Image (cartoon, coloured by chain):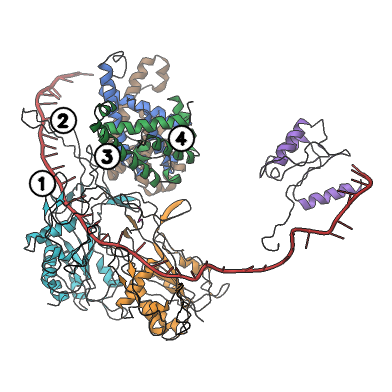
Chain colours: A blue, B green, C brown, D orange, E cyan, F purple, G red
Amino acid sequence: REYAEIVYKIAQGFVLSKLSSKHDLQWSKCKGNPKLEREYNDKKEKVVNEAFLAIRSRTEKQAFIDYFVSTLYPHVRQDEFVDFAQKLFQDTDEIRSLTLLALSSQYPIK
Amino acid sequence: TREYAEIVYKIAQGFVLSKLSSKHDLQWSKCKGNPKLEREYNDKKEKVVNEAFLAIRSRTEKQAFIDYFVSTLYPQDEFVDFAQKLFQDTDEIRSLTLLALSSQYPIK
Amino acid sequence: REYAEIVYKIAQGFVLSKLSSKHDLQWSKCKGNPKLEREYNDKKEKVVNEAFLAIRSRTEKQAFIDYFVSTLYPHVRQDEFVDFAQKLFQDTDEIRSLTLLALSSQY
Amino acid sequence: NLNLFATILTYPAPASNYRGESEENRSVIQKILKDGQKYAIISPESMRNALREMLIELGQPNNRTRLHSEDQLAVEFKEYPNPDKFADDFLFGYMVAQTNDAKEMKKLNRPAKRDSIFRCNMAVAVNPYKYDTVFYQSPLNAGDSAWKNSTSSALLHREVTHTAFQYPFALAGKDCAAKPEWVKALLQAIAELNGVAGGHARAYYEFAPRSVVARLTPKLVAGYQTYGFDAEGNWLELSRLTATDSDNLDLPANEFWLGGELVRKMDQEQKAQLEAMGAHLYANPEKLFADLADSFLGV
Amino acid sequence: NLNLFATILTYPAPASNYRGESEENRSVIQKILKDGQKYAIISPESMRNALREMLIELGQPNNRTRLHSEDQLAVEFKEYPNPDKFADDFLFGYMVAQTNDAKEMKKLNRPAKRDSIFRCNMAVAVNPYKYDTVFYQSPLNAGDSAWKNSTSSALLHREVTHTAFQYPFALAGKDCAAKPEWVKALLQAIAELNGVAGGHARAYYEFAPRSVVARLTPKLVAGYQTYGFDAEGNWLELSRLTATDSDNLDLPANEFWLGGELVRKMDQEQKAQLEAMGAHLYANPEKLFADLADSFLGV
Amino acid sequence: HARAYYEFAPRSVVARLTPKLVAGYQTYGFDAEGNWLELSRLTATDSDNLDLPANEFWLGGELVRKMDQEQKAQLEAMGAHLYANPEKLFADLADSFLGV
RNA sequence: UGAGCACUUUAUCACCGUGUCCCCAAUCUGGAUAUUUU
């Protein structure tokens, strides 16, 4: 619920941050364009593809990747849910299931 | 009806169509062009559907969790509640997905 | 367990001490104009992010580097040092999962 | 009379056993689950064949020898199962249900009844994961030879699992005619227990026992929790604390026999402490079986 | 009769083996895990091909030669597998399951039974990390030549791991017709064991053995913990302490043969101390194989 | 039969009424392995706290003896709604019945 | 709480068995320029 949308929120923030690193943060140059929109989604889809590929490769390292590698490169955000930032130490599997679900939804390719 | 029925059916047909157009790089327009290209396209779809059919049965019960093959077949606001609905009582979702796969199975 | 919040709480005091050290007049001038905060926010961002690379470099000396840095800033360290055997006999649990991901990647 | 029964486990190793006989594209090994988790494999009757073969190599009569000439396996027999002229596969004259009748019961006075005098159960692993492959492949010859195997090429994979697993068994028998030599040979042969699950030239596994424990050899059947010790951790040491406690104050102890692993790496002071009767502590498991057979058999 | 079985390990080095045959963008090497950690790789059947090739270069008959002309690999054959006229790939006349029948069993009296007389298992690494890349790349020719490979450019990476890994095996055979020369050649060839996992022009690895240890050559099968020694540390020295102890007081010892690494850098006084029978201490591993083959074979 | 014997032990026996003929709950029309006792008469009495006297018609259900007992008691009445065991329950029924 | 209104669907017991298969490893490819003050 609230954690699920939190996973959703960080998914958008990480994607746009990667876009900011590679190109402009704001998205208005690609409006009604047959080429600018093409490249904007192309760089979008390749960034999430490689990030998702790295995450799903560490299948059996469920717990450790959730401590170390799956949480440094994605810039995470925390406001008050320190108490709920505890199941990451004992669940370590469903949180991954949520993350892959969120990244899969953020695949706007037809 | 924005319910589980069409949602799983849409993702099932979209999943199989996407990766066959990725691995084999084929479109239905080329399939209908000549009978020759159609049959191996049907044969290629035959291998694609059955490997998932057998393997999805391989992992059963709660050990399937909500993590599936190629990361749950890589499926906005409706996603939040729908994910929670499938969060608990997951037994029926997997069972009804086999119906979609059988539906996608080519006839004859 | 309880040390997770202890590491959590001491980190905000650590970064607040960080902000109070490099920057002057602290948050009292925030009400002046939102402009100066942007340089304060970007500077506070550009100091933590460079520390990210150093803190996650190598387990053995990332200990040695962070003891001396940690002993400097906070003032309630006397409470924590005398308790739980100085972070459970020096290096345990890879420094609390790398200082709880540098305080959850700085909030 | 004395009744004995024991439990063993083998050393950890990778393993895989042909168990499907169902499909060719993929191989399945998992058999039965526990408490919502699938961590048990292996059949309780293959080791019977392994024991039969090993008894064959030890010089006892070849009463029933497996032959491989037809497409489907068939096993020959001697003139008739007889538990007196020969070992009868440890006196295993079994049921012969046929309409011909004319059995030896009316000629040799043989009721065709069994002498089981053996008890065994299926083994259980201690590791749950069975979702890994190796992805080997098979070629097409196409070498213009007189024989073509499949006239195709396939990319088929196999599943393996690295696990150690335990094994209980019971005997609860008694000495009779020609028994002491045969039971002694059985106890000698159970020590090695090689060649399990038929031939395997690609995966090689052994049933050499470590941390063998036998319970209540002189007393009647009172044992409990045969599947106790697991997770590479000793568990019968607290069983001695709670069942037939070492001191004879609130719960008098009993004659136990312990294996090698549980004493090889364990507290030195405990050996001296566990000396109410001294129990039976041995370094190699094979050493204690001879003495146990001598004591239980009485000779 | 005598039965022997041994374990080896190779020197540490970087390595990588084509093992996926699944995807092109990335390569995966990891196969099987242990106790919640992924530190094992390599297949238990490629070394069979390596042994076959090496036996080919040693002058024994070329019964089954791999040919590479078609897109999918196919292997030719001689007139028919015969374990008498020739070595039959160490007498490996194997199953021929076909509807044609008309096998040599009715003509040459060949039951098609394939002698095995060999045992081997998959190797296991000792280092767990498999999350590093090298990030090479492939170009596009575009040189107006008659052949274009991919008509594209890609940035694809590969994974390598620096590790040393152990290897067990067993023979448990017996001398027969034409065997002593063939088993001697096999023992000679196992010393080198080069060209593993096919061709590799970018990563070069060797299976030269160090710290080889063979167990219980004259006695029946009693060995245990084949995967024992690891972590660049000796472990069979305490095994001699606990299994067949050197002194013949509480546990009589046994004839063992030890490799070179375990004695090259080890206490000088221990050599003199380990002299209840002297065991078998050698500097280079290849030296001891000839003597071991002479002793076990009997000639 | 002796083997596989079934015995009728009391388990949440609840019903009462003033000197008037039976009505209301009809002793039937109830769900299984649930709170038919509870749902039925708690809903009726909440609807009929003033229509029927809950003081004489004591509590219902053995499960409510474990949770929310205080809330139900305070919202309904302070009557002789004791419910611990059927034996002492019938004991106090007999005690109150000797006088009537 | 009224007249046709009874008394029980009652008591016992084994499926014997035995027994699993061999065969196999591919390929190629790298990059360019650039600092100053308290």
User: From the image, which quarter does the C terminus of chain D lie in?
Assistant: bottom left
Mark 2 belongs to chain? E
Above or below residue E166? Residue D74 is: below
Magenta span: chief secondary structure: loop
Name the residue carrying label 3.
C57
Q: Nearer the viewer, mark 3 or mark 1?
A: 1
Identify residue type, mark 3: Ser
Identify residue type, mark 1: Ser
Residue range of the region highlighted in magenta in the rendering: D19-26
Q: Which element is circle 3 on?
A: loop
How far apart are the alpha carbons under marks 4 and 1?
64 Å
Instruction: Evaluate whether label 3 is on the same chain as label 1.
Output: no
How far apart are the alpha carbons under marks 4 and 3?
26 Å
How far apart are the alpha carbons under marks 4 and 2?
47 Å
Name the residue carrying label 2.
E153
Labels 4 and 2 touching (C-beta < 8 A):
no
Whole-percent x and y of residue F74?
A: 75, 36
Q: Which element is circle 2 on?
A: loop
Q: Which element is circle 4 on?
A: loop
